[PDB]
Image (cartoon, rainbow, N blue to C red; front, side, top):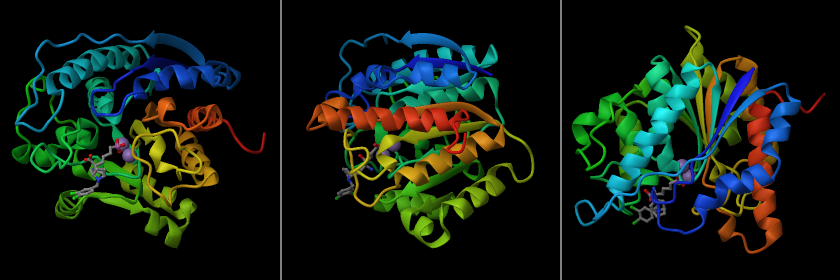
Length: 306
Ligand SMILES: N[C@@](CCCC[B-](O)(O)O)(C(=O)O)[C@H]1C[C@H]2CC[C@@H](C1)N2Cc1ccc(Cl)c(Cl)c1
Ligand SMILES: [Mn+2]
Ligand SMILES: [Mn+2]
């Protein structure tokens, strides 16, 4: 009944300017009214300002902004933890996907038995030793998964993080651009995923059925939905940093969100990677933002049948 909205204008998990304007873009697309109309009591935390870190040199000549991303996530986790502890379902607007380190950490701080539904073209599970880009937004899951920590070096600014997710407690949906070390990780740790190919075969209804059976088939658990807008086909969500052809249709995305709502267990949601500056037109920017609002609203009960 109660929803907290937090703007997290992270951009330092990656290298493209503009994703810090995602939260404003999503708000301007009418998020707050849409949620209110659904009966959500709202607490708006506004857009957070994160503490800068002087001299945040690369880590290992490769990983960018680790102290800045680490500290921003620590601060974000504090806000998320507080909101969830006060009884709010916590919606965080990104910002790049490295913020999931903070939202999931903060969420788990109040709800340790949470499970994660990760909707994304990408697995975001590179470690600092496997990333080819050095961009933390392609690594957040590696810092969160319990089974991987012997393979994850300690980054400056990251010491506060305690891995809070087990490999059996996250399911990916949407995957179509997975790096070879990520594929190894997913297979070696038996992490379950439904790639676009699996969706082509099963259909989104069976995908959602199987996802919930894996995560909440044995017991009810609070659900953390981490939704990267690039899960959608680039024709629908062009304003994003790493678009990949052959993504979710509009209807598939809504269906995912509807099924999330239908569990009655949604406890926190990330909507990340909307970058209005990468739109070639104001129309492309607005449609991406409108789509983000649609995902969030559907996750909190908007239906297509009244
Ligand atoms: N895994 C990425 C992309 C992460 C995107 C993060 B997000 O939050 O938007 O899902 C990364 O770690 O940076 C990949 C790196 C690389 C640049 C963009 C895309 C994805 N590329 C895949 C790729 C391409 C070429 C090579 Cl040689 C390799 Cl190893 C991997
Ligand atoms: Mn992605
Ligand atoms: Mn992502």
